[PDB]
Amino acid sequence: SDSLSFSFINFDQDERNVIAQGDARISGNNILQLTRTDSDGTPVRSTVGRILYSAQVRLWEKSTNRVANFQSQFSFFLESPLSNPADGIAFFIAPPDTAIPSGSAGGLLGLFSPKTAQNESANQVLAVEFDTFYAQNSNTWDPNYPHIGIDVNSIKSAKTVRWERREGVTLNVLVTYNPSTKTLDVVATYPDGQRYQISVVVDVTTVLPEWVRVGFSAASGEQFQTHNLESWSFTSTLL
Amino acid sequence: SDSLSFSFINFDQDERNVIAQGDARISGNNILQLTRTDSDGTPVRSTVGRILYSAQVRLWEKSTNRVANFQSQFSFFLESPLSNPADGIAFFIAPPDTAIPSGSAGGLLGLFSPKTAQNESANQVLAVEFDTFYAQNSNTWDPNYPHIGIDVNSIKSAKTVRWERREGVTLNVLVTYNPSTKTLDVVATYPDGQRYQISVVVDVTTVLPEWVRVGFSAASGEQFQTHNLESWSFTSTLL
Ligand SMILES: CO[C@H]1O[C@H](CO)[C@@H](O)[C@H](O[C@H]2O[C@H](CO)[C@@H](O)[C@H](O)[C@@H]2O)[C@@H]1O
Ligand SMILES: CO[C@H]1O[C@H](CO)[C@@H](O)[C@H](O[C@H]2O[C@H](CO)[C@@H](O)[C@H](O)[C@@H]2O)[C@@H]1O
Ligand SMILES: *[C@@H]1O[C@H](CO)[C@@H](O)[C@H](O)[C@H]1NC(C)=O
Ligand SMILES: *[C@@H]1O[C@H](CO)[C@@H](O)[C@H](O)[C@H]1NC(C)=O
Ligand SMILES: [Ca+2]
Ligand SMILES: [Ca+2]
Ligand SMILES: [Mn+2]
Ligand SMILES: [Mn+2]
Image (cartoon, rainbow over all chains, first blue to last red; front, side, top):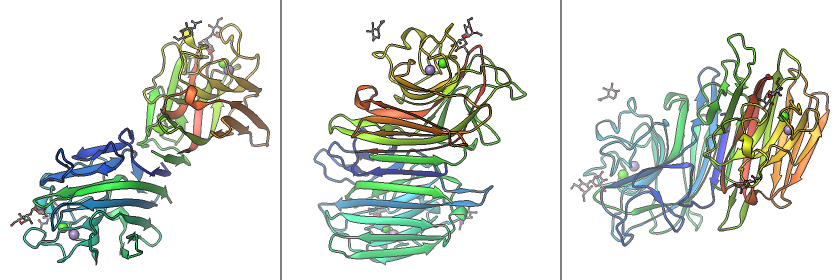
């Protein structure tokens, strides 16, 4: 269609218009939990979950040279009982048939397969990652610190900014795409006003198909944490 | 979710987020055609078609006493080579599992079954009808003229206004529900400024389930016409 929007002030477990993949679920307490927990609510190793909004977004139209804008606002928090929590949460855009790739329960954030994770020609993923785990022994593509990144068909972010994950604290995020400037902008803020900004010039018509779904992905490998989405609103208009 | 909106400036045959029922289709020339035509494009007898937007609207929430507003704007035109064309087109709201009932290809507008069409206790349909056929020999519930009506769980409109269908002319329609006044308002206009207004007080929480789908229905029995939707935008916010 020419435009689509939705808003979740909170999520409820009855929500009809989201697609859960892997370990993702909306809890009975109204939190969207992307990764698995044991019966005590403790995060566990080797888990991946994603959610997609069910309606399919017209990101661009080849026969008319129309391109959509979009704006995605959301808030999340992460918790872990241990040091060096992993692996992170991402807002992402992918073809509507997208599924969790094998080998992605870890630093690939549920978004990529190991043999092609850095191969821009192979992937169909645009993502904004909140990447808490950076160890060189397995995340060779990361800078040596937790970071916010924009991922264009690769797990190696096109651009990153330094970000110190705060245990249990809500981060508020606004992601916007402007097709006239071909700019994808991210602004994230913690409650004290600390602000994180990352932006990339990217022509969405060369990185993604005409129809897409939007959503979130998270994963934990050998290190773990809960990945908790509290709210989400989205709008897209084909211009 | 807490809100949802979409817009079709035009329809395209590739549209991913609509559900076609019966004879409905979006043509290669970008018109949403609800009822069947022969190979020359001529309307035919005994046809019914409906479309639904795929995303499910939260019309109300019982555990929080929240009720949604909504606003639906659309335009349509009807064509027939013969006199007394039939049967009409309706915007409607129904449970998400809704399907064309048997016996509805005619004056029941694809919305009701003959034995219960006037039984408010049985149905789950809220509709705004543009009803072109009124013959007492089969449409006993209609006034003796073409009319615009608001249908609350019955094919006998709660309220009607006189309307002379114009062959091939676009009618523009705005339908709005205000939950604070429990008022469903319809305003329709022809290109010369002729205006049709109909409004009913109705508590949507007593006539429809908490989750619904929205869309359009049309049918032809022994008399026929094409039922052509040109554009449609919709918004709903749970208050
Ligand atoms: C504690 O294990 C760390 O070091 C191991 C090698 O000594 C790695 O195999 C291991 O990587 C896995 O877990 C990390 C952290 O969750 C994850 O990013 C990666 O994709 C693997 O699943 C880890 O770095
Ligand atoms: C030309 O047929 C008209 O009169 C018949 C009886 O003499 C009716 O059976 C017939 O009704 C069917 O067609 C109408 C018009 O399309 C429709 O409204 C009704 O639901 C029946 O399908 C028609 O009135
Ligand atoms: C990257 O993926 C493309 C598409 O399959 C492939 O042609 C190319 O060989 C890959 N690059 C490498 C280094 O394997
Ligand atoms: C109307 O439908 C209700 C619900 O099934 C039913 O109880 C009632 O008998 C019907 N009324 C008539 C007149 O048949
Ligand atoms: Ca990482
Ligand atoms: Ca009628
Ligand atoms: Mn990273
Ligand atoms: Mn009528």
